Image: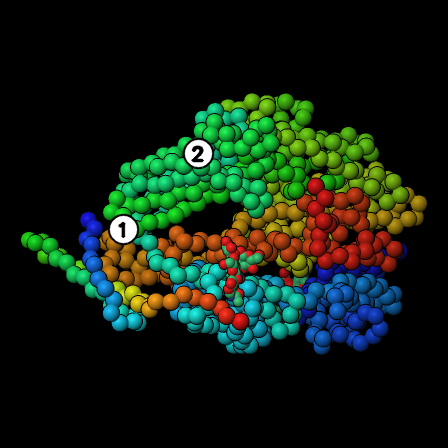
Amino acid sequence: LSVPYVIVPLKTGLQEVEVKAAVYHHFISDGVRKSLKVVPEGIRMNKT
Amino acid sequence: SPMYSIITPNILRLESEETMVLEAHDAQGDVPVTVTVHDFPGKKLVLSSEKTVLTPATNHMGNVTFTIPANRKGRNKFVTVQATFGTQVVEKVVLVSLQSGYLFIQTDKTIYTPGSTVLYRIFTVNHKLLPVGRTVMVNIENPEGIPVKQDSLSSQNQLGVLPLSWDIPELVNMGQWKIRAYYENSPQQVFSTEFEVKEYVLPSFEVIVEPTEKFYYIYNEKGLEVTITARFLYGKKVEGTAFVIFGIQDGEQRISLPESLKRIPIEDGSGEVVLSRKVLLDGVQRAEDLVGKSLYVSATVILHSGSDMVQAERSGIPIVTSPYQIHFTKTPKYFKPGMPFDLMVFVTNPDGSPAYRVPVAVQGEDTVQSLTQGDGVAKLSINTHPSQKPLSITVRTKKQELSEAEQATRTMQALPYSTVGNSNNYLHLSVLRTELRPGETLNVNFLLRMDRAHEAKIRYYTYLIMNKGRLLKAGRQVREPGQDLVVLPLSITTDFIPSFRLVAYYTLIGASGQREVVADSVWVDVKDSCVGSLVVKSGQSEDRQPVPGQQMTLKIEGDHGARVVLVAVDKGVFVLNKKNKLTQSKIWDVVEKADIGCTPGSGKDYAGVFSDAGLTFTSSSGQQTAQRAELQCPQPAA
Ligand SMILES: *[C@@H]1O[C@H](CO)[C@@H](O[C@@H]2O[C@H](CO)[C@@H](O[C@@H]3O[C@H](CO[C@@H]4O[C@H](CO[C@@H]5O[C@H](CO)[C@@H](O)[C@H](O)[C@@H]5O)[C@@H](O)[C@H](O)[C@@H]4O)[C@@H](O)[C@H](O)[C@@H]3O)[C@H](O)[C@H]2NC(C)=O)[C@H](O)[C@H]1NC(C)=O
Ligand SMILES: *[C@@H]1O[C@H](CO)[C@@H](O[C@@H]2O[C@H](CO)[C@@H](O[C@@H]3O[C@H](CO[C@@H]4O[C@H](CO)[C@@H](O)[C@H](O)[C@@H]4O)[C@@H](O)[C@H](O)[C@@H]3O)[C@H](O)[C@H]2NC(C)=O)[C@H](O)[C@H]1NC(C)=O
C-alpha cells in the first residue's frame, strides 16, 4: 500500500526524511530514515 | 649415431621459469651437458648457468629450469639457446614475450553516483596465476579517455593484493569510466575494467526477459514468444503492468517496431508477450534477408502503486534457419592414412553457448551416431584408407523432432601426415575424451605405424606436456618389439587446468641410413574449475531469514594459507548493470586465449605436429621444426 507525502525542501545539502509506522494489536513497527540530496536551481555547462 | 635433441616452449617468457628438455639418443655412458642463453644478435650472456649430465639410468633425458632476467620499438626480440652436449653443440633461436603476467581489477559496485567512493583491488599474479611482488601503475580515465588519477604502488609483501580507493567529485561527466593498470616492466600490456557513473536510485525489484527459444526460426508461424518475469529483490513475486516492445538490430543500428508495442498485465510475478511473425515482416518492406540479423526486447514494468519502475532488455536474439551450429575448431586438420581419425564435433546454439544432447553423424555410415556432452563436444571416430588423398568429412546433426531441412551441416578437409622421405611411418595418439577432472587418470594410447623391418628399432616414446604455455612434464614410454599399442597411465593433477597438450615422438635409423623423426600431438580439455576450492555458505546450520541489523555467522571453506577478499553488494545494483563482473569462467577464457597451441592435434608432418602443439624440435641430425616468428596463432582462415 502506497502512502503519498507532499514536502518542500527549504535548505540545500543532504537533508533527511523520516517516516515511522506501527500496527494496531500486533506489536510490530518499522521506521525509515533515508537521506536525499537537495540541489538548487541551475543547469550544467562546460564553458571553454 | 648419437642424436642430441632439444625441446623448449615455442615462446619464452621474461622473469619466469621455462623448462628445457634435454636428450641423447644412441648415446653411451654419461655426457656433460651445458646449457647457455645469449641475447640476439651478439653475445651478452643473459644466463650461462644450468648444466646437467645425462645418465644412462634416466634414458639420457635432462631437465634444466632457467630464468631470463630483465636488464631492458615494435619489433620482437629473440634469444639464442645453446646446448653443448660434451663437444657437439646444438643451438636454436626462440621468440621472447614481454608479458610478465596478468592483472585482475575488482570494483565493489558496477555503477557509481557522483560523490561516492570507488573501492577497487588489483590482483598481481604471474603466468602460473601464483601471486607475485611487482610494481604496478594504475590510472583512471573518464568517458572521453582522459586520465585523472595515477598511482604507483607495489604488491611487495602484500600477497598479490593491492587495495585502493578514489572519490568521485560531484562535478564530473557521467557515462562509462575505465581503470587501467599495468606492470612497470611492460607498459605495452595494459589491463582495464569499466565502471559506469550515473545519477541513479536502487529499485526494489528486478525484471527478466526470457524468450522461449534462444533464437528465432524465420519459418515459425507462432512467432517470437517472450516471458516477462518480475520479482522483488527479496524474492517475493511482483504485481504490476509491463510495457514490452521489439526491434531489429543491424551491426550497430537498431530499428524499433512501433506496431509491436504491447501492454500485458503481470500476475503472480509473471507475464506473457508474443511477437507475431506478421508484425515482424510488416516492420520491413524476402524473409531470407532478415536471416543473420538479431531481435531485441525492451520491457518496462510498473507496480500497481506507481511507486517504482524498472526497464529491462534482452538483445542478441539470432534469426537463423537452423537451431544449431557445427564447428571443427576442436578437430585436428590432419589424419593418419589407414588409422582411426577422431572427430571432435563442436555443436553450439545460434547465440554461441554449447548445445547439450544433440546427436551427430557423418555423411555416410547412417548407423554411426554420437550425442553431445555438457561441454558441447561430441565423440566421433572414423576409419581411413592407406590413401595419400585428402579426406573430406561432412558432419550432419541428427536431432529428431525436426527435419532434414532444419538441420545444420558443415564440411572440413583433413590432409595425410607426410612421412620423412615418404617412408610411411606414422604415430597416432588416441585419447578417451571425457570431462577430465583433477585427480583422475588418463589412458594415453600410442599407436605405431611402420613396416616390421624397422619396428624393432623403436623402444621408447618421448612425450611432453604443455600447460598455460610452459612445459609441465616430460618422460618416456617404454615399448617392446611387436607392440603397436601401449598405454600411458598419465595422472591428472590440479596443474593441467585448464587445457593441456601432449606431444609424442620417436626417432630411429632406417630407409637408407637416413635419420627420421615422427611425431603426433593432441589437445585435451580439463574441467573448468578452481585450481583449489573456495566455498562461502551460511554459518547458521539452521533457522530462516535474518532481520536488518542482526548478526550472522559466515562460513568460509578455502585452501590453507590462502588470503580471501570479500565484498557484499545489493542485487538491485545488478538490475541496472550485470556486465563487466568477475567470474572464474572468465579467467580460464583468458588463459585459453593466451595458449601457444593452434591446433586440436596432429599435423602435416613431424615438424608440424610439434609446432601445431606449441613446441620446437631440433636435433643433431638435422630434423627441425618450422620456424615460428609470429606471436598470435594463425589468422583464423575459416
Ligand atoms: C624435471 O625437473 C624437475 C625438477 O628437477 C623434476 O621434478 C622432480 O621429480 C621428482 C619425481 O617426479 C619429484 O617427486 C618426488 O620428490 C619427493 C621428495 O621430496 C623431494 O626431496 C628431494 C630430494 O632431496 C634429497 O634427496 C636425497 C637423495 O635421496 C636425500 O639424500 C635427501 O635426504 C633428500 O631426500 C628433492 O630433490 C625433491 O624434488 C623434493 O624436494 C620424493 O618423495 C619422490 O620419490 C619424488 O622424488 C620431485 O618433487 C621433483 N622436484 C621438485 C618438484 O622440486 C622432474 O623429475 C624432471 N622431469 C620432468 C620433465 O618433470
Ligand atoms: C561538454 O559539453 C559537450 C556538449 O556541449 C559534451 O559533448 C557531447 O555532447 C553530446 C550531446 O549532448 C553527447 O552526445 C551523446 O553521445 C552519447 C554517446 O555517444 C558518444 O559517442 C561519442 C563519439 O563516438 C563518444 O565520444 C562519447 O563518449 C559517446 O560514446 C549518445 O548516447 C547520446 O545520444 C548523445 O548524443 C556526447 O556524449 C558528449 N560528449 C561526451 C559525453 O563525451 C561533453 O561531454 C562535455 N564535456 C566534455 C569537455 O567532454
Task: Where is residue B520? Give x, y as percent.
Answer: 74, 46
Given residues B322 and B395, the one toward you in this image is B322
Give left or right: position of B1 versus B305.
right
Look at the numbered disc 1 and say if its residue's Cβ is closer than 8 Å to ligand 2.
no
Q: Residue at x 81, y 32 (%)?
A: B389
Pointer 2: what residue?
B259
Specify the quadrant of the image occupied by residue B417. Answer: top right
Pointer 1: what residue?
B307
Badge 1: chain ID: B
From the viewer's perspective, is residue A1 above or below residue B354? below
Q: Residues within 10 Å of mark 2 (few under 14, many from 20)?
A: some
Asked if residue B493 shows in the view, the reply is: no
Dot 1: element: loop
From the viewer's perspective, is residue B106 above or below residue B332? below
Q: Residue at x 30, y 67 (%)?
A: A38
Given residues B524 and A11, the one toward you in this image is A11
Give left or right: position of B321 versus B563.
right
* Count of numbered labels shown in the rendering: 2
